[PDB]
Image: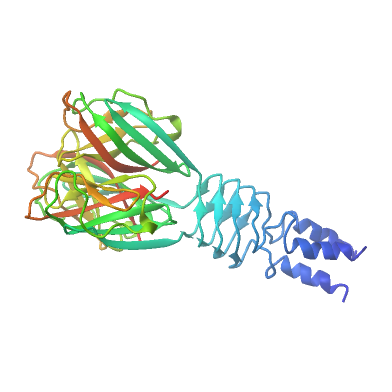
Length: 149
Length: 149
Length: 149
């Protein structure tokens, strides 16, 4: 019974208890800090969040952020009725996806050489910075990427 | 000899054994989960895989994916003989690099203002969505980025 | 006093000592390797470094790299006085942000359909690959992304 302490300790040195081990699937809590190099050979799974935005004018926008920091933007739909400098007219970018500093992402017009970009800005509005688009709409594709913080 | 258990345990509390320690270089196996914040100050090394594609029409394409999720695309070569809507004619994107949902990446024509984009789609075909290109080829550069899953 | 060894060991199996635990905030040193899948539910914080470059001709360039590998480029200012093929005239990209292989990032001209790209190359020079720009300057925005190694 004095020797159980030992047996039981030679068990926590293998799995169970509050000890992280060199094998098994385990869970870990708290602000871990790693000063040296680290490596993952398998899959590392950072948190994901995705958001759909009808930016207005016909401009669809699917944003996909991972670990709150880098978000990839996928341009869809078709824009119409905007001036060279205008702030887009539809749904704003949600708090969770809004940049700290302004970020211009570059889209392209489907089946054309003409191009455009839009500014996501911290407040979450999206100003347009392509040429003045007429009532007759043009399809807008292309992927953007910006650091959230 | 009763006290060796102890000595030997006060060793696994330092290194060796199946225990992860606050120092040394160690290896770890199994689906580790980290509920709290984590930090790396050194280098974190996620798995890398790179792929070269002759998309056809003269369009070179070097894809580089890291941790199976985000791949950066580097456009090379020069495209010729394609319509505004056509599916590119050469080697398809391999299974390991194929998106779940379609992704348009935006390239640019070297020494010109004219631009283009192409669609990588889940099956791995690459449809072209720039203007109709004549027999006389044009050089295509620019980097794209898309989430694999 | 023989039993303190035990008490003291049943403490290092909880926190303190050189042992990583399933709870608390701890620090870790050395080349950790993770063969299995890993997961982070909170925030994972990779090292960050940001750099501002006056590329010359009026082309501003803010580069932001994370974990030394992927850097997002933010184009600013306005370019003027460059030929279709020229190497930009102002401050070069610093060693810490210079790619191994050349990377073209695609910018866009503010309030226009016209587009451009520039080549960051390993030595750190930035060759321009848009159309020949006159003395009258044009504003240049858009975000790029390239793998550093």
